[PDB]
Amino acid sequence: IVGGRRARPHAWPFMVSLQLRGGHFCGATLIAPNFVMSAAHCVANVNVRAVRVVLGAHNLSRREPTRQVFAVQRIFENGYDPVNLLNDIVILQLNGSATINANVQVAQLPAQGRRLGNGVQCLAMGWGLLGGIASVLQELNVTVVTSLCRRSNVCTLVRGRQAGVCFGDSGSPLVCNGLIHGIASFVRGGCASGLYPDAFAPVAQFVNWIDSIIQ
Ligand SMILES: CCOC(=O)C1=C(C)N(c2cccc(C(F)(F)F)c2)c2[nH]cc[n+]2[C@@H]1c1ccc(C#N)cc1
Ligand SMILES: *[C@@H]1O[C@H](CO[C@@H]2O[C@@H](C)[C@@H](O)[C@@H](O)[C@@H]2O)[C@@H](O)[C@H](O)[C@H]1NC(C)=O
Ligand SMILES: *[C@@H]1O[C@H](CO[C@@H]2O[C@@H](C)[C@@H](O)[C@@H](O)[C@@H]2O)[C@@H](O)[C@H](O)[C@H]1NC(C)=O
Image: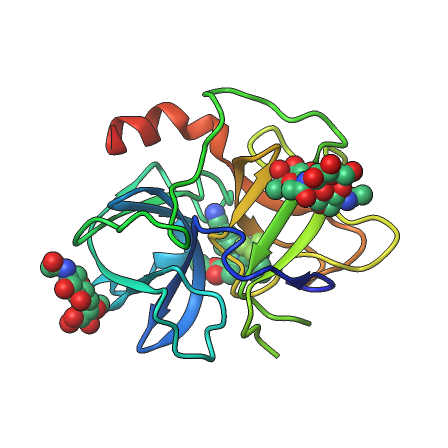
């Protein structure tokens, strides 16, 4: 996250860190005790048997007792199309069930087909590049836009300054009106261009599919 701020510890207990040999590479969202959802591009060309799923984290540079660590049991995809940058969603079924507590909670999703108007205020977040990489979870105020976007993405922009998601924020939630409306998918013009809106997978379009998998 470029131009964001540190989150209050555990303010976002659905927020997940996807890791290889101890290092963050992508975000995810806890959507049920034994399921997270991320961006399909996070896991493409990655051996998932190597991925550690980290719930309850805040400072990735610190040893944290609040954490719960899982392996990926199974993955579900929905027509990931990297050429067109479409359907950038993946569900990762965990090798066990999260212990739901103060620091580890399941996110709330919108209803199928639910659309966001131009000018809705959302929050982006993640452990990605700061402009080094983040130790503490960062958050950022962003605004939903349609100029330079498509119907098959939720796009957001910070106005009046250069701020936005960046490398390592991929897969992370976008929270709008208390609901997970986006999964961080792609940037144009590099990170925090001040010209091109950030693009997220439109979680509302995939709600029926998500529910059929989790329940
Ligand atoms: C195959 C792996 O590619 C990447 O890792 C990409 C990354 C990180 N970002 C990327 C970079 C910075 C921040 C983010 C974001 F928005 F997810 F936080 C994504 C990116 N930007 C533009 C193209 N890409 C590609 C990309 C390719 C296909 C799709 C789809 N569908 C989405 C992104
Ligand atoms: C689920 O897996 C947890 C951690 O698994 C670890 O990470 C993966 C990616 C591999 O490196 C694996 O060898 C590691 O053990 C366990 O701590 C936990 O006990 C598992 N839950 C089960 C099977 O009940
Ligand atoms: C910056 O963001 C703050 C929090 O945003 C609100 O809560 C999050 C979790 C989402 O549900 C989002 O839709 C909400 O707007 C706001 O309280 C604050 O007013 C924002 N400031 C501005 C001017 O953007």
